[PDB]
Amino acid sequence: ASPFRLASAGEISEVQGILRTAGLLGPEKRIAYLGVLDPARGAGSEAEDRRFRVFIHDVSGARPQEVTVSVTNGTVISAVELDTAATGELPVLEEEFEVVEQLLATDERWLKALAARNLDVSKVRVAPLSAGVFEYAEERGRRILRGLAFVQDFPEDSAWAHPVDGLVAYVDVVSKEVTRVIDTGVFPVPAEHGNYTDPELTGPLRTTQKPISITQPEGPSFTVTGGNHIEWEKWSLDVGFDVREGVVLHNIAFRDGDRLRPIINRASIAEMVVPYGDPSPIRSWQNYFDTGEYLVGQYANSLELGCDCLGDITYLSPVISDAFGNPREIRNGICMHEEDWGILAKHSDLWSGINYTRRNRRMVISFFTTIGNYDYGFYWYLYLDGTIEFEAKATGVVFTSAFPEGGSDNISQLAPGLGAPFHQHIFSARLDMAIDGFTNRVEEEDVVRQTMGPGNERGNAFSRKRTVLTRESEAVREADARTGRTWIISNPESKNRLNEPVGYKLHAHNQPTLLADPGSSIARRAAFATKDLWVTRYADDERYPTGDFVNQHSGGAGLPSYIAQDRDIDGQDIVVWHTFGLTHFPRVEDWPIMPVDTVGFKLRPEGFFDRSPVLDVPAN
Amino acid sequence: ASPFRLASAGEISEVQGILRTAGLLGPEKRIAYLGVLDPARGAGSEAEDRRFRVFIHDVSGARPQEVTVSVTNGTVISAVELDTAATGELPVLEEEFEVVEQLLATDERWLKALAARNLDVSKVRVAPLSAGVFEYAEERGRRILRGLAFVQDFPEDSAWAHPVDGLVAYVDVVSKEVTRVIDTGVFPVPAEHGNYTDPELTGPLRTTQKPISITQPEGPSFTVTGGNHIEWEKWSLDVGFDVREGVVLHNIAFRDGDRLRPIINRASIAEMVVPYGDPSPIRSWQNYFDTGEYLVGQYANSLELGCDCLGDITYLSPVISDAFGNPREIRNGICMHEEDWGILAKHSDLWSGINYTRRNRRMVISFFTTIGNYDYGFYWYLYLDGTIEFEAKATGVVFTSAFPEGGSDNISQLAPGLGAPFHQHIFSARLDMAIDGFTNRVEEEDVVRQTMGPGNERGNAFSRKRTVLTRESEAVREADARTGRTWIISNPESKNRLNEPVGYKLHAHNQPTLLADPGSSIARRAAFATKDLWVTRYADDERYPTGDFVNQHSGGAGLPSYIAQDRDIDGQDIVVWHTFGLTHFPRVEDWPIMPVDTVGFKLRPEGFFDRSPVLDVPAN
Ligand SMILES: [Cu+2]
Ligand SMILES: [Cu+2]
């Protein structure tokens, strides 16, 4: 019944049939993206209309199309031919990955480079990586991937231990031709293996860990209705899944007495970029837009009970489309569970004699994705006290290079001859806000120091100040950890019982933003990553901070274009875009497989409630 | 056997007997502090001499003494008379807190002030607070507490809901004299109650929370020997307890194959200050040194199984002295347990076909203290991967005032007429480092941005810079979140297999430090709180960042005086002092009892190991 229900296998098969009968899905076509469209703004929309957006690639070289389909009515709503030299290429297809290694395997320049290094071509794996936009004019309007080589000594070997440095190739994956092979010199291929399941490397496994058993003998405290609607401890929300963004949270609201109060209309990780900081020409082009170029949802893991998710777990198994329009189920792709989170509130009072302790809990909604060597977990948390938190967990295997004789200012040494280039992992959270409704505003809050003097004779006073962001041209903000800077999203038309506007406060981790030179290609294509906070006026088609077609787009799309409209955001329907990320100087302990590191943000109520919202939590 | 064992009841009784025999503990004497001294530097020199340090107060007004005794040999080692007007008063005694309300109940100035407000003296509670050092010359050399008043409507009422603003009194607790009563005008006493167990306020309790059962069917994975020596998942340490500092960690080490490798010799929270930012003369003197003035270990809670600590819990019950030298057990005052901590490492490799997931866990050592309206939890965490983390949890009831008509720049409104002054909670961690032994140094590490140009033609390169701190005069450092600043403690004489010095990296939360004006009394007394990081050369008598005697002591002691010696810290026995804190602008949701907020820091290995230290963790 809900317009926010997950796509079903039958809906995807119907989309396939509609495209096929319209002549839009011949043997030369590939679906590069397929997703449900959210309902348009309308708090009275009753007519059910399930619409899907599709990007259609053509392997023979014809121009791609963007198509919108109505599943409800069985019709094609619109079909537009795309000029990719202008607006960007379509996302990378899974089937184009293996093409890169196959094409190089018969190219005489590639084979010459391997022969000089005494490498068997059958043992050389090629990582197929997005191309970006640099100095090569012949690439404009063509689908390019670039390849970096790794040696796999045997089928179960970790090829990441054996980078082949000084060599890179560029490939047109539609015309199937190798455009350039660049060989800058011979580097020894690091020889130590990185096989973290080899007993020779692990040593004897520990026998000292005793079981931890986490059970819920009466079942979990949340309910799931209509497939993806969650009710838990006064929270209400819908769990969506999109092949580009992954898990998406809709209609986050809190039941305060008899009122269901909205907080966030839609929450997602709308882009993530991994720029590398090694100036070697072998890698200086390397920037992963994992969301926009690769689509993190289609690489979601199936999560195993007792290993990936521990406790009383409820799974969702979302459905996506393959390249031909067939539905594909990601079995156990989303984990949902509640967990204990320590003490919530505690006080032992001498005067009243009352001793009071209550425990906290959080609801967890998570998925894990694998893109090449990296693995990322995406975690959303809801807490009893109204706090909302996101956490990204980074693990997997670091991307490697040779470690140069004489050292490097831009590469860490992990093992003899083995390097790991410096890089960042930067995320953009898109928060379509709805604090008690859609009339919202953002204030920047700084601590204010005061000078000792009249009215402050002991020099102890301090204060704070709030600045309203009133137009998009002034809503591009930087962090300032030294002044305790936070941002408050409030509703100026909804007051608490003290006659103050209700609000939520965003707490950032204040990690460094994009480090690349402002004039670089990556600073232009990932402009969102250069600032901590952006606020835009809501619009239906402003979905991603990097624009719709990120792959090989020359730059400036997404947030810089949106902000340029300079719309009023003071008490309007607004969207907060928060940049946060990890700056990774790899350490020896990250090798041969990296322990998790984390980054995130949280939002806490700020006068949203009339008092603490967890006074009705029992003692148990 | 171990020199680091907890003080026993018998040792405390023996100290009492030794002091009595020496003529130092007659009926007019009180013990204000008693604690065991750590062994001096010298690997097992003293065979074992258990020594105790005692501060002895005299209720008749004679000068106090600092005494060191050997319980092993039954002797007083030294006894020194203290000149408290010069070097500071002793910590506040529990029995002095009761004196204040009773003395005020008979003072005609106090009664006249209450009669002016139509208040019944029998219902007025007085919060007795430390005095600090301000403009009152008659206080020098005297033990003073200051009192603020709150109305308790009935014996189970939360008096914090009913502050009596505009009124403060100062009391000499030795001569039993009210020195001053200051009345700046009548404020209405806020009338709403704050009784968070009253069903009228809580509403009906939730019935929705289902149980979460955490058990360990085979028992925990750690062992406890010698009363307080812990071994868990390659970690080794001793858990101490001091009445001033609370839980102290000694001899933190990691078993790396065959070798027990030291990391931290002694870790503690060596001071904590809570400065208030309201310039009203009723409260502009208000600063709590909870550790230095009150002694946080003395007020440790007994922790209840299932409420305070959940899971398979091992308890320690430390012994302290009462004011007469009798032993007092804090039953179940320390909780120890291990917790699941999600995914440790994960990778699904396309090329090798191997899927790999491992789970993390952490060892938790915690205690909770209650001082007046505030309750603080202190948590130390050890992780499988070598990470050490500290977390403070702040809860309890916020300190209140009237809310002025016309508002305030320094006070939050919580309820009609009820305010909460702005304040901070600032901690000092004292980390006596021993990274692979005692030859250590500290480097400051900043991210370095690079300009596009020769050798960085695409503008993507970034790097980092490390600066060795070589002398104490240059070892007073501030945070810089924007450049990703961290600090590395390394051993220049101990190298990993890549021939790089082994190290640990300190990651701060980069919260604001002390906000008070630099010329204020509190900035001079809490100078440590004005900077994020200090490094000193180890010395036996340099224990607290505020000095030995904080109560009513002007500046002149502690970290600024230590640093002036300008000692060599480049490859020496060094101590890291890290300042971290919360800046608290109270919100409506903090009333009537505050949900936990947290702050802390962590240390992560940085080339300490030759590869990931958790390759031998089994799959389970
Ligand atoms: Cu990384
Ligand atoms: Cu506070």
Image (cartoon, coloured by chain):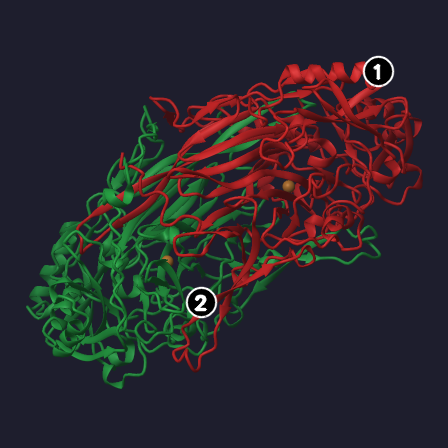
Chain colours: A green, B red
Q: Say left or right for B377 vs A184.
A: right
Q: CA distance from mark 2 to mark 1?
A: 68 Å
Q: Which of B94 and B239 lies nearest the eye of the viewer?
A: B239
Q: In the image as oriented, which residue stretches furthest toward the bottom? A: A137
Give how far across and how far down residue B131 sits, in percent. 81, 37
Q: Which of B153 and B92 lies nearest the eye of the viewer?
A: B92
Q: Residues within 10 Å of mark 2 (few under 14, many from 20)?
A: many
Q: Say left or right for A611 vs B557.
A: left
Task: Residue A273: name its quadrant.
Answer: bottom left
Residue under label 1, please give it.
Answer: B26
Task: Residue A610: name its quadrant.
Answer: top right
Which quadrant of the figure shows ligand 1?
Answer: bottom left
Residue under label 2, please give it.
Answer: A514
Q: Say left or right for B463 vs B414.
A: left
User: Of circles 2 and 1, which is in front?
Assistant: 1
Query: Image height check: is A69 above or below B178?
Result: below
Q: What residue appears at the point 39 percent right and 56 percent down from the top-left corner?
A: B498
